[PDB]
Image (tube, rainbow, N blue to C red):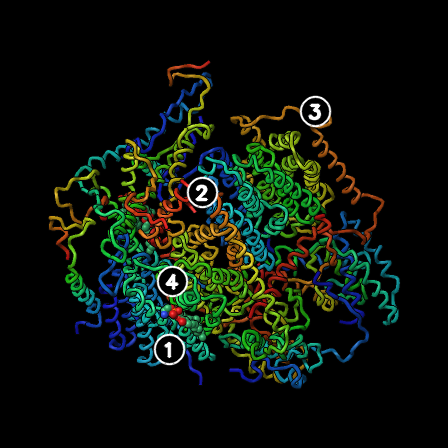
């Protein structure tokens, strides 16, 4: 993380912590531009300690008095009912063993199920042809070419390209 | 069935409901309808088995034992006479268990009968039940020789302490 | 053949049970006891030895 | 129980262009790229959807949100939109 | 109907369990152990009265 | 209490060449996903971080061990310590109860059970 | 309309289970239940005290029960 | 180097080992395991005769107590097992 | 059948730079604040080279943690520090140590 | 005419001197609570037909909940203390199948782990009082216990009191109910209102012919329930969930009933249980339709006013919330008023009356808090307003309750055989001022809610002491007792 | 046993005599037919005692104990067929015969009529169990655990021959437990202390203590193929009942030195429960549970005076069915995941919903749900040692509280998400996996209907 974008990680949560405490909507909305004037103290300057002392005093009065049980937007890392839908929980590929008269239903769905597998069954003449080439030695985050230079299939095929939908 | 002297209780003494009011009460509508919807599927079938169960009879007989020796026979290291005395003593103990269960529910006959007074009456069961269980653990409960069952070799020897140390070593009773 | 590997082997139970009465028929020591179990005059304590 | 399709977000991303009084309703609809219109123009432009949508807007959502239709693109991946 | 959906439900187990109580009091020496009268006057179930 | 936990510090420009410690793990992550994505695996990953975990915890602690310090002989203050103390409680017990059971009486007379 | 396809692992072996569990337990449990009803009605025991049984007592079958 | 067996599911059902006559391994353990032991053996100890001579001593306790309650006989005696049969050595 | 550096060994100063990472990559090049020096204090039955303890700790707490699964659920590859106490434990909140509850019970 | 009964159906195993078979009890609680307990469950499953309407796992719920009635009903019908121990644990094992309804969810399964932890402390106290009856009283049927009262009941009844603290949410075990709310909503409407918390004090109610003497008991009992009131009052302040606001409010109801034991008032105490069971199974379900209407926030934030095409359920709340102010003449008036005015003649700590009566205001300010923040102000919550209140399945449930709810304390207490002597003296400056205590709670909350809404803009200062909105008890004990015993005291004396 | 050893020895010339794969269906078929013969001639009445025939059988009169001994052989053959079928047929049949031979000595044992036939049968085991650990086990460090499986039980049991023949030449003859009517008392000496010491210490080798029990999480950790003889090792540990035979008589009055066996088995009781909440192995997880409430029964015996023999009769079979059933759970979920480490099993409860009921009721026998066969005996241990003193409820009650966590510590490990892995572990719990998982609670709660037969003299 860099020093300039360290301002941005605080700036969104500076106002996000405030609407936890408000009672109206305009009461929170009146303090948006009102807090903006403090942000408009040093508009554009150098990147040295003058920009760090604006953040070094943003240690206090940001963590100091921070969010007394705030809003959480319940579908989140925290919050209630964040992972509540777990009786279903999307067991993708639980459907290998059937021993049919249980595979009687959905006839066209299984006919398409084996169809997509040939896209995964034939990708390593193309994906592994660039997997040895795109990585220089052992370097950074290893996504492929996002078109794979002819046809990107996927590169992340198929557990990510057919990833779990929510309900 | 049983014998009523074994399980006594005072007579029932159920009073009159005393309605006294011309208001409609629901108790004159419940007992006048529900009695016949029970007597038809139960009592007639109970009568239908009653003639059918009397088709044949089967006998089962009392078991009365034989008790020739009691205590002091025989000599120390023996086997034969000291086996029947075990059959004497041990079957003379399982009788003495459920005799207390008769007297225990005899207390329970008084308590769920009065209820309101329940302590200052019935005149026996706080006394007589404590004239049994108090006269029980002495010399008939091998405390704590009940593990090896104390079979004729400690149940007499508590009673040796109940005669040697007791009643003579009171200095001088 | 007629499958001696099969149920002929549980037929050894009564083969053991036929031998199981030989020990009791030589344990004929005492009839005269006092647990009634008396062998007084009857053909009931004599039997099943 | 009420479902949702592609047409709801195509209203709202275009609507907040006119809701914010700094941006006139004469820009481009889906691809304005936001540089022709540092803080408070990559956060304030999505601080309104913090009020309306508000699914906490993670750290990678800033550097993608220049292309204003690329804003709309991954929401259908998140909100699991039709077909 | 409301003819057998409740009749199989409630109307059948009535007779079985009442037979299990009428064939119970004559066998067990402690049947129902109903309490005392709680009567303030003296009434017609007795012969005397109370003021 | 447990902890402060010091979620903020200083930078700019302490240890400029310290970065790309993710290059250690992203090479393993590339080795992870290439092992993870294949048309036929039918089995678990070897995952040697759990192999080196339990076997160097359940076993290979007694070859590590030596009684060259008294803080390894410190377990005398926890194992045999209270084990004398419960008996130091219990030896004082059961005899004071017995003397009141031998000399004098305190029990109810209907104590058949027990 | 909103119509999709639910994802279940398998229902074949699981509903194949509880079949012979239920089947064989009624293959001999339910037929043996009639003998517990037939011996209740036609067969009893009576009564007590003592009987004298003559001089030599009765054999085994001293029980107050049908099958005991 | 390494030869091993995996999940036995060649789209058949499978009970213990394989298709045929090993198919009979189901109904030799379903029918012999329970449904004869868990039924007839469960019935056998249900009405099994008097355990430790108890049911005699149930009604025998009903008889003798009222005979002590008949004339004069005290109850829970603990009466030294017919006394004056022990010399009782003092010291 | 993995025999080469199958577990820890009698460390921690048998050329500790050649420990991490010839195998058991807890440190990248023995300067990552996770070189296998942290044998607490040895002599005891603690961990030796032990790709183990005093590395940065007190929580895997199931964070946002998107660059892999990587928090506690979804198997990052080789970052084992300590376990079996953390599936139910967390990081620091906004207040601090002050035991006012005993004063509140006062 | 009474005719209380016991039965003698079928033998269990018998031992040396005592034989327990089975029996039942039909005295003052079987002919009272059982038509009350069934009426609630008869009126609660129609909401679960609507709440759990999208789940193909619907059939497990109606199956699991019915057996939970069996362990709740066999306890009150019992008269053998062995049979009480059956129901004492049977109620908790169903709870792990109810908080653990939703799988995963790394706090809720931990909340299932937090649930059974504090239940076992209440288990070890009850068995201690059991074995003392074996050593002396020769049985543990409830008859022969009340046949002769012993001298030293001080040693057994503390274990009876410690058993009450396990499930009736006393001080020290207080995070058990605010952690148990994490499951589905009519689950928690059953778990917290009329089941799982009345049986924690019900066992004490059966033990009334002994609790008169042994004066170490009564001072500990009434002082304990006084602590449970105001710590739930201070931690409920600034709480941002609807279900959590109602979670504390049943606990201050428990603070009443603990004190009602130390004063020798058995049946007036139980009559407060007779009224209270109506209340929150309505209220969580009435508030459950509000949360399902928005389908994801369940916060007191972003609610709006009452009248956003919401006529009926707002009328249903103000029936309940005004009763929750402290009963001027509403549902539980014949139970709440006859106890705090029975605190006139007492022998208390006198810190107790300086602690129980203050929470009557703190109970009243719970009412308007959902009026002033969810039913009063301007409409604000996120868009696509998909509200719906038209389902006669829910309309059948609400209409069946409020007819019985208002006539709860006014029909049952209208016809009852009397048991004790009333107060009948309530002097000057000492009689009804606890109602006035409720009145000022409307005033004090007004000049905080309106001041947080319309003021001279009191700017958000970061300086406050906020060890009140947390309580500081879950902050450290959930970080220390699974740290000392689990790690250091184990791995030292482990391998 | 008139003819109980007699039919089962004829089962032995049937394994290698038979055909091919028919040997599994044939061996199970004959085996259940003996189970009725066990039930029939036994369970008779009953009042002190049933001396059976002669000098080889006393009919197990006071404690039946013998029905449980005969379930297991028609119960493990269906379990051992998980991973055994890779060898020659003549080598696999030898593995069948040695387990059948294990039952025959134990059929004559538990009745045994005597004491000089007891010890030769008390040591008649440990020969077939040791061979099972050596061949067809798991990975290495087997052979030291085979040596720790010796050199303890044999180390402690040898002074019994020093003790018993010293009794046989002194006072009468120990052929008959019922000719033990004359028993001289034993006073406090410096010779008689050792006489009681050798009489007792060998029985602490099998049912463990806080000391000398390191071998017990070796045979259960390093174990045969899929819990095969591990189920038999459950009966091997509980089968040290012979303290009930011996110390009921034959120096009963030495209780002055009972205390360090009371105390050591009591603080070690509460300790070894918590010694496994940070364990990382499934087969070690049930193993330390099997120490704790098996160490509960020892203070029920050295403390005499029944209302203690009542529950201790039932507490032997309490985990004897339960821990055998837990090992059946642990023998499963290993043919599908080939490592026994519990942490790798995240993301269960969704692939196998049918066996998820069986996880619930099994661990519901440790909380134990007081109308069962588990909390019906633990209340009598409460009923005994509270009459000893008032302190004993404390350390014994926390044992009921630690295993409340320690059992649900396993159940919650099944519930996790997205499972990260597992293109294997497909198999949705076939017939062998769930029919063998049955027949454990199916007699257990059945015995809770009329639990009259599970009672000692007592
Ligand atoms: C097509 C139609 C076909 C028609 C079929 C025939 C019609 C039905 C038959 C009539 C009823 C018989 C069935 C038995 C149940 C009722 C028993 C009864 O109450 O009568 C008393 C009567 C007792 O006889 P009694 O003359 O009154 O007195 C003798 C004793 O002294 C009495 O004292 P006790 O020694 O018996 O002690 C009491 C207690 C004690 O008994 C025991 O618990 C001992 C058994 C466990 C011992 C431990 C074993 C551990 C290994 O007995 C009980 O357990 C009674 C509880 C109910 C029976 C238990 C069911 C087990 C399955 O019957 C019995 O209890 C005998 C028990 C035998 C159980 C057989 C079970 C058969 C089940 C068949 C399968 C049905 C499945 C249906 C499913 C439907 C879909 C869900
Ligand atoms: C160490 C061994 C301790 C043995 C000391 C000597 C014991 C002895 O002399 O015998 C005691 C006594 C017989 O001798 P006595 O005193 O004369 O009695 C009259 C009969 N002549 O009576 C006896 O015979 C007692 C017989 C039992 C004592 C022998 C066994 C004691 C050793 C068992 C301890 C546990 C095993 C330790 C070794 C294995 C572990 C390495």
Horizontal and vertical percent position of residue F104 = 49, 44
In this view, D10 is above or below B67 = below
Check if mark 1 and mark 4 are on a common chain. Answer: yes
Residue corresponding to mark 3: J427
| Residue mark closest to the camera, 2 vs 3 | 2
Q: Is residue I53 left or right of residue A92?
A: right
Gap between marks 2 and 4, in whole Å? Answer: 32 Å
Instruction: State whether residue K3 is above or below residue J137.
Output: below
Q: Are marks 1 and 3 in contact (CB under 8 Å)?
A: no
Give the mark, 2 or 3, whose residue is nearer the N terminus: 2
Q: Chain of mark 3?
A: J
- Whichever of callouts 1 and 4 sits on the residue coming sooner in the sequence is 1
* Looking at the image, residue B119 lies above or below residue K336: above
Q: Secondary structure at mark 3?
A: loop
Residue G15 visible in image = no
Say the numbered circle drawn on residue K243.
4
Residue at mark 4: chain? K
Q: Tell me, for residue K131, which label it has, or none.
A: 1
Residue J465 image label:
none
Q: Secondary structure at mark 4?
A: helix
Q: Which residue is mark 2?
A: J140
Determine the CA span between mark 1 and mark 4. Answer: 28 Å
Q: Quadrant of ligand 2?
A: bottom left
Identify which residue is drawn at 82% across, 60% down: A60
Q: Which callout, 4 or 3, points to the residue nearer the camera?
A: 4
Callout 2 touching callout 3 (CB < 8 Å) = no
Residue F80 is situated, as x and y percent measured from the top left of the image, at 56, 66
User: Which chain hosts label 2?
Assistant: J
Q: Is mark 3 within 8 Å of ligand 1?
A: no
């Amino acid at each position: 993380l860099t020093h300039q974008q360290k301002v941005l990680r605080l700036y969104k949560r500076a106002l996000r912590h405030l609407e936890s405490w408000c009672i109206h909507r305009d009461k929170y909305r009146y303090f948006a531009c009102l807090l903006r004037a403090r942000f408009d103290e040093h508009k554009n300057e150098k990147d040295m300690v003058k920009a760090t002392q604006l953040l070094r005093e943003a240690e206090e009065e940001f963590w100091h008095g921070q969010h007394p049980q705030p809003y959480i937007f319940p579908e989140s890392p925290g919050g209630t009912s964040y992972e509540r839908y777990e009786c279903y929980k999307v067991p993708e590929w639980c459907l290998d063993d059937w021993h049919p008269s249980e595979k009687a239903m959905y006839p066209d769905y299984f006919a398409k199920r084996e169809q997509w597998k040939k896209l995964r069954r034939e990708s390593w003449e193309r994906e592994v042809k660039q997997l040895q080439e795109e990585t220089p030695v052992g370097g950074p985050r290893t996504e492929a070419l996002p078109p794979a230079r002819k046809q990107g299939d996927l590169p992340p095929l198929w557990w990510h390209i057919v990833t779990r939908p929510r309900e | 069935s049983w014998d009523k002297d074994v399980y006594p209780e005072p007579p029932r003494r159920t009073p009159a409901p005393s309605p006294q009011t011309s208001l409609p009460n629901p108790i004159t509508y419940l007992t006048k309808a529900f009695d016949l919807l029970v007597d038809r599927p139960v009592t007639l079938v109970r009568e239908f088995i009653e003639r059918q169960h009397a088709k044949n009879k089967y006998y089962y007989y009392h078991r009365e034992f034989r008790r020739v020796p009691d205590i002091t026979e025989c000599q120390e290291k023996d086997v034969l006479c000291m086996f029947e005395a075990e059959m004497q003593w041990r079957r003379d103990y399982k009788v003495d268990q459920e005799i207390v269960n008769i007297i225990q529910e005899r207390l329970k006959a008084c308590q769920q009968r009065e209820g309101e007074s329940h302590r200052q009456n019935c005149a026996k069961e706080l006394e007589q039940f404590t004239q049994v269980v108090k006269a029980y653990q002495d010399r008939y409960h091998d405390l704590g020789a009940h593990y090896s069952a104390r079979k004729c070799l400690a149940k007499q020897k508590q009673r040796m302490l109940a005669e040697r140390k007791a009643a003579k070593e009171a200095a001088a009773a | 053949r007629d499958h001696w590997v099969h149920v002929l082997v549980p037929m050894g139970f009564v083969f053991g049970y036929y031998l199981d009465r030989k020990n009791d028929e030589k344990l004929t020591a005492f009839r005269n006891k006092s647990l009634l179990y008396k062998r007084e005059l009857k053909p009931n304590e004599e039997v099943t030895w | 129980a009420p479902p949702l399709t592609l047409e709801g977000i195509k209203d709202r991303v275009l609507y907040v262009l006119k809701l914010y009084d700094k941006i006139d309703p004469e820009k481009l609809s889906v691809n304005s790229h936001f540089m022709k219109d540092d803080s408070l123009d990559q956060v304030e432009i999505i601080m309104a959807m913090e009020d309306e949508f508000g699914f906490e807007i993670p750290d990678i959502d800033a550097e993608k949100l220049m292309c204003p239709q690329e804003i709309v693109d991954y929401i259908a991946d998140k909100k699991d939109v039709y077909e | 109907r409301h003819s057998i959906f409740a009749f199989t439900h409630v109307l059948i187990p009535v007779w079985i369990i009442h037979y299990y109580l009428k064939y119970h009091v004559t066998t067990k020496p402690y049947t129902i152990v109903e309490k005392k009268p709680r009567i303030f006057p003296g009434d017609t179930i007795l012969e005397t009265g109370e003021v | 209490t447990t902890l402060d936990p010091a979620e903020y510090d200083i930078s700019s420009e302490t240890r400029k060449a310290q970065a790309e410690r993710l290059a250690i793990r992203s090479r393993l992550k590339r080795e992870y996903q290439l092992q993870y994505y294949d048309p036929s695996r039918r089995g678990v990953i070897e995952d040697p971080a759990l192999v080196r975990w339990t076997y160097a915890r359940s076993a290979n602690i007694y070859p590590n061990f030596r009684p060259n310090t008294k803080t390894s002989l410190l377990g005398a203050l926890f194992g045999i310590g209270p084990l004398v103390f419960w008996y130091y409680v219990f030896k004082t017990d059961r005899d004071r109860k017995e003397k009141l059971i031998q000399e004098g009486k305190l029990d109810r007379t209907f104590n058949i059970s027990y | 309309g909103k119509r999709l396809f639910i994802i279940k692992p398998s229902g074949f072996y699981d509903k194949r289970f509880l079949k012979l569990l239920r089947f064989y337990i009624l293959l001999t449990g339910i037929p043996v239940a009639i003998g517990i009803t037939l011996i209740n009605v036609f067969i009893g025991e009576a009564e007590l005290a003592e009987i004298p049984e003559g001089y030599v007592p009765e054999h085994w079958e001293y029980f107050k029960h049908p099958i005991s | 180097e390494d030869e091993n067996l995996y999940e036995k599911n060649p789209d058949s059902h499978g009970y213990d080992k394989d298709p045929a006559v090993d198919i009979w391994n189901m109904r030799v353990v379903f029918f012999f395991g329970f449904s004869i032991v868990l039924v007839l053996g469960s019935t056998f100890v249900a009405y099994l005769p008097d355990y430790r001579m108890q049911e005699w001593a149930r009604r025998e306790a009903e008889r003798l107590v009222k005979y002590r309650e008949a004339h004069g006989l005290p109850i829970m005696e603990s009466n030294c097992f017919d006394p004056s049969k022990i010399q009782l050595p003092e010291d | 059948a993995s025999h080469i550096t199958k577990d820890m060994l009698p460390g921690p100063y048998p050329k500790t730079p050649e420990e991490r990472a010839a195998a058991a990559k807890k440190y990248n090049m023995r300067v990552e604040d996770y070189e296998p020096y942290p044998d607490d204090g040895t002599g005891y039955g603690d961990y030796p080279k032990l790709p183990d303890r005093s590395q940065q700790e007190r929580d895997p707490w199931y964070d946002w943690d998107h660059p892999d699964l990587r928090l506690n659920w979804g198997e990052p590859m080789h970052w084992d520090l300590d376990m079996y106490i953390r599936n139910r434990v967390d990081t620091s909140p906004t207040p601090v140590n002050w035991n006012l509850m005993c004063k509140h019970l006062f | 005419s009474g005719q209380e009964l016991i039965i003698s159906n079928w033998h269990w195993l018998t031992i040396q001197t005592l034989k327990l078979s089975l029996s039942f009890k039909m005295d003052y609680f079987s002919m009272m609570f059982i038509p009350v307990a069934l009426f609630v469950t008869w009126s609660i499953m129609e909401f679960s037909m609507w709440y759990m309407y999208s789940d193909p796992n619907i059939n497990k719920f109606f199956k699991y909940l019915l057996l939970f009635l069996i362990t709740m009903l066999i306890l009150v019908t019992a008269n053998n203390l062995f049979q009480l121990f059956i129901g004492w644990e049977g109620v908790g094992i169903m709870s792990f199948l109810l908080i653990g309804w939703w799988y995963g969810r790394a706090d809720a399964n931990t909340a299932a782990l937090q649930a059974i932890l504090y239940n076992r402390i209440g288990d070890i106290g009850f068995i201690l009082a059991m074995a003392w009856f074996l050593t002396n009283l020769n049985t543990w049927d409830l008859q022969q216990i009340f046949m002769l009262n012993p001298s030293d009941s001080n040693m057994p009844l503390i274990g009876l009191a410690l058993a009450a603290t396990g499930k009736s949410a006393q001080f020290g075990l207080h995070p058990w109910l605010p952690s148990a709310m994490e499951g589905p909503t009519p689950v928690s409407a059953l778990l917290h209102s009329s089941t799982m918390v009345v049986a924690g004090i019900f066992l004490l109610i059966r033990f009334y012919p002994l609790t008169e003497n042994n004066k170490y008991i009564q001072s500990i009992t009434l002082c304990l329930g006084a602590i449970t009131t105001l710590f739930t009052a201070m931690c409920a302040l600034t709480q941002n969930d609807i279900k959590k606001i109602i979670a504390f409010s049943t606990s201050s109801q428990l603070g009443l009933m603990m004190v009602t034991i130390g004063i020798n008032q058995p049946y007036l105490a139980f009559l407060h249980i007779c009224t209270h069971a109506f209340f929150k199974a309505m209220l969580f379900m009435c508030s459950g339709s509000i949360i399902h209407s928005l389908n994801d926030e369940q916060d007191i934030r972003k609610m709006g006013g009452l009248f956003k095409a919401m006529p009926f359920t707002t009328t249903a709340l103000i029936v309940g919330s005004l009763a929750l102010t402290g009963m001027p003449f509403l549902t539980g008036f014949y139970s709440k008023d006859l106890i705090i005015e029975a605190a006139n003649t007492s022998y208390t700590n006198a810190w107790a009356l300086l602690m129980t009566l203050i929470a009557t205001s703190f109970t009243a300010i719970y009412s308007t808090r959902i009026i002033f923040f969810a039913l009063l102000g301007q409409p604000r919550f996120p868009t696509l307003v998909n509200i719906n209140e038209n389902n006669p399945l829910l309309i059948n449930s609400i209409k069946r309750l409020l007819i019985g709810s208002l006539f709860a304390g006014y029909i049952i207490s209208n016809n009852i055989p009397p048991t004790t002597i009333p107060q009948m003296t309530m002097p000057y400056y000492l009689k009804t001022t606890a109602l006035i205590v409720t009145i000022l709670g409307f005033i004090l909350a007004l000049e905080i809610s309106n001041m947080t809404k319309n003021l001279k803009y009191h700017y958000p200062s970061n300086a406050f002491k906020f060890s009140t909105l947390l309580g500081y008890f879950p902050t450290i004990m959930h970080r220390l007792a699974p740290y000392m015993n689990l790690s250091m005291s184990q791995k030292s004396a482990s391998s | 046993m008139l003819k109980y050893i007699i039919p089962t020895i004829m089962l032995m010339p049937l394994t290698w005599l038979s055909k091919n794969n028919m040997i599994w269906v044939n061996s199970t078929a004959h085996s259940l037919l003996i189970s009725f013969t066990s039930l029939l001639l036994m369970n008779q009445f009953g009042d002190n005692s049933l001396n059976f025939s002669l000098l080889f059988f006393s009919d197990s009169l006071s404690t039946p104990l013998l029905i449980l001994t005969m379930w297991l052989l028609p119960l493990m053959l269906m379990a051992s067929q998980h991973h055994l079928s890779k060898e020659n047929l003549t080598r696999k049949k030898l593995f069948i015969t040695m387990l059948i031979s294990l039952q025959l000595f134990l059929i004559m044992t538990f009745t045994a009529m005597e004491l000089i036939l007891f010890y030769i049968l008390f040591e008649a085991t440990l020969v077939p169990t040791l061979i099972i650990i050596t061949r067809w086990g798991n990975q290495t460090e087997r052979l030291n655990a085979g040596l720790y499986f010796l050199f303890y039980t044999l180390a402690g049991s040898l002074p019994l021959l020093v003790a018993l023949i010293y009794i046989q030449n002194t006072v009468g003859s120990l052929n008959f437990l019922m000719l033990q009517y004359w028993v001289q008392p034993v006073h406090n000496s410096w010779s008689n202390v050792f006489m009681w010491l050798a009489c007792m210490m060998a029985f602490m080798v099998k049912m463990p203590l806080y000391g000398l029990h390191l071998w017990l999480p070796k045979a259960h950790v390093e174990a045969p193929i899929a819990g095969s003889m591990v189920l038999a090792a459950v009966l091997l540990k509980l089968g040290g009942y012979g303290m009930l035979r011996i110390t009921l008589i034959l120096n009963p009055m030495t209780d002055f030195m009972a205390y360090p066996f009371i105390m050591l088995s009591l603080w070690g009781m509460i300790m070894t429960s918590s010694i496994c909440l940070r364990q990382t192995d499934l087969k070690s997880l049930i193993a330390y549970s099997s120490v704790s409430h098996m160490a509960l029964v020892i203070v029920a015996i050295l403390i005499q005076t029944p209302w203690s023999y009542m529950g201790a009769t039932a507490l032997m079979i309490a985990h004897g069915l339960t821990s055998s059933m837990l090992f059946c759970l642990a023998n499963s979920n290993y043919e599908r995941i080939h490592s026994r480490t519990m942490i790798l099993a995240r993301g269960l409860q969704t692939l196998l919903p049918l066996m998820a009921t069986w996880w619930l009721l099994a661990s519901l026998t440790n909380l134990a749900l007081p109308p069962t066969i588990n909390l019906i005996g633990e209340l009598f241990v409460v009923m005994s040692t509270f009459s000893w003193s008032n302190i004993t409820i404390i350390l014994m009650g926390v044992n009921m509280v630690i295993t409340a966590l320690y059992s649900l510590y396993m159940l919650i490990m099944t519930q996790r998400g997205k499972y990260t892995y597992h293109i294997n572990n497909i198999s949705p719990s076939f017939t062998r996996e769930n029919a063998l998982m049955s027949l454990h609670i199916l007699p257990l709660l059945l015995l809770t209907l009329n639990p009259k037969i599970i009672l000692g003299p007592l």
